Length: 236
Ligand SMILES: CC(=O)N[C@@H]1[C@@H](O)[C@@H](O)[C@@H](CO)O[C@@H]1O
Image (cartoon, rainbow, N blue to C red; front, side, top):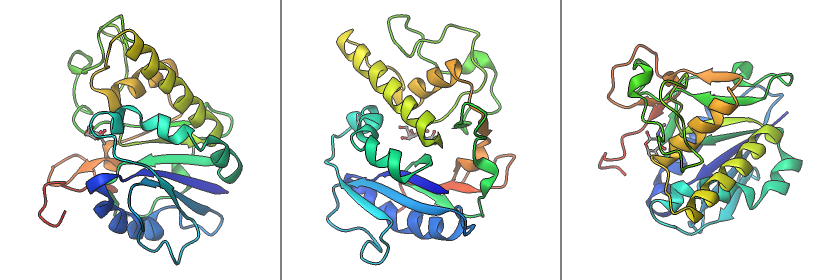
């Protein structure tokens, strides 16, 4: 089975590629049945272990700056959609500063008879009531979610599923992003708002706990499986 990792590390975020990659080569899908393809969108000339591992696919991408780096995130995946359709069976997106600490296996693969989508609970909202979810509340936006509706507050730092269903998600959100641009709207706060809208219409087959998005330094009711490295640490 072929597992595709989508990874954007333009500008000052390629410092995060090395330790992410090593942790991933160690803890992520290390059953010999799986093969891992890294699709690394960056402006870096060379990536760590690129000359050794043929599954590291460097794709050229410039820094768009904030927020287009976060707003056109799914635009970036779809420029190589055909390559993904023939080389991968599952796709997973990870934030640059994410870090694996414990083994992860087939338990996070959405079953083929489901919608084949995976979402992850945001660490700042897992214990909050519906009334405090910061959804997009403007009916003029494609990311609109009325008050009282919604189940979880999903995050944008980790999402995926089977390649077909996920590219379908990429295609939809791009359209939502573009339609709002015309109507003179930037959805707030975008990396999570559009995906929370999509996961409302399409309740994901798998919902990961914030143990898969554990912010460094926090005290949460979970063992951290994936850590969100503090960006403001001096070593970065
Ligand atoms: C994992 C998670 O939810 N992280 C998101 C991620 O999208 C990041 O870019 C930033 C906001 O842009 O912080 C957020 O919490």
